[PDB]
Image (spheres, rainbow, N blue to C red):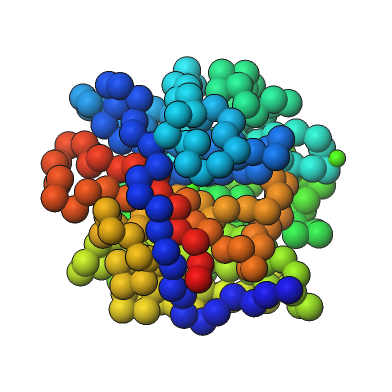
Length: 303
Ligand SMILES: [Ca+2]
Ligand SMILES: [Ca+2]
Ligand SMILES: [Ca+2]
Ligand SMILES: [Ca+2]
Ligand SMILES: [Ca+2]
């Protein structure tokens, strides 16, 4: 068994895939182990003004991601969260910019980018002091409760909860603000995981921040998903993952993605002995506007 360190240091792959022809970027990755392989969903931006979602074909090795297929979704599930909700034998794809503040689709075969149900409401509430409104949800459960976490591009991280029996369902309208900092410091792309192999419940939160050298992640930890969060690696010079410690040669940004989860279920479990981050990065010298930033997947592996 292993523990999470209070500071982090990684090595990185190069960019793992080029976007489908006609797309500018692949973003906001969510991944699960599936069939002994990896199943990845993502945001895309085209080479014009439009957003969508996609999945990759199954692939076994991270170096196979470059030749995995890229499958555009008919239902746009921007900034998706993929997981298997084991208690009801159902796969969940949570996302934003759907019919309500957050939405989810259901499926029995998550490999089919276009085999999902029509949307169901995941969250119908709003937040104060945000120009974007709610963004970048994730969903995670323990033995009693399912939790919704999200951001607001406003320095704040939010949480909603429901008894686990009630899921899949709408978390409702209410949320609690659980962290608040400068806007750049707790910006977006929040993720929460159960650290496996621990003698007491241990949860890891990462939040994307805007740094002087680029996008990076700050980490927080908690003893309970419904408890308070304490900063862990939470500065740009000693971050969870960023230019300071990523070993990434092709990107300064370490941005919206997913730690590599050890199982696909709602506990969002990670193996601290084999910590890896599937992130979005981009060539530092290409800085177009219009949301055309050429984000690509990359993989950090914890030393
Ligand atoms: Ca985004
Ligand atoms: Ca089951
Ligand atoms: Ca996400
Ligand atoms: Ca209210
Ligand atoms: Ca509230």
